[PDB]
Amino acid sequence: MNIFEMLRIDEGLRLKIYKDTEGYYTIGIGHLLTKSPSLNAAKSELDKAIGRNTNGVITKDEAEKLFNQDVDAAVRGILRNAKLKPVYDSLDAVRRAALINMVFQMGETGVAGFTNSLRMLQQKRWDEAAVNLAKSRWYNQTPNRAKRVITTFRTGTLDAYKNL
Image 1 (cartoon, rainbow, N blue to C red):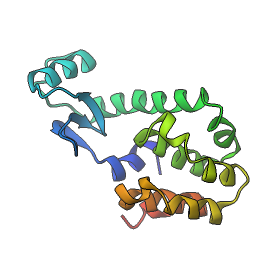
Image 2 (image 1 turned 120 degrees about the vertical axis):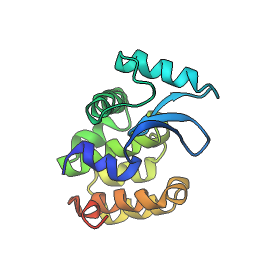
Image 3 (image 1 turned 60 degrees about the vertical axis):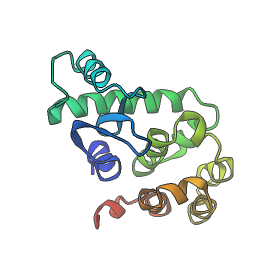
Image 4 (image 1 turned 90 degrees about the horizontal axis):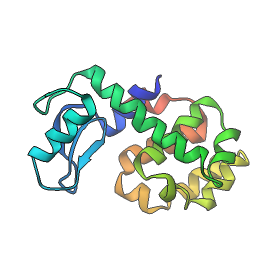
């Protein structure tokens, strides 16, 4: 029901440094720290961020704190993008987040590739934007969350996060 708890369902929430798929040190809600194998480099960058010898463990609060900036960096990139902005503006609240989710996960540029589906959405072509979506590298990597996003675009209700 809220931007934070929506990405919790997807990215998941970890209050201790862990490694992503490719073995990256990250914490909280998909926040990356370092790409280097250092365990002492992640904590470091963690303290720098939190601003406190956390010893690689944070509080819920600190996560949201990192979350919001992660989220602003997502929005800021959209705002400064010729292909998403328009689309973004055109969307309702419920669909603005489905939009921010992809940029949270893929990135400003990456999401700036789906011009096929980009346009249909701006045009309110839900049922059909959903289709080009399904046929995508994205859908096949994290189909779990991807098909959740697509539904919130398809409908405009955040119901997909109401069963899971």
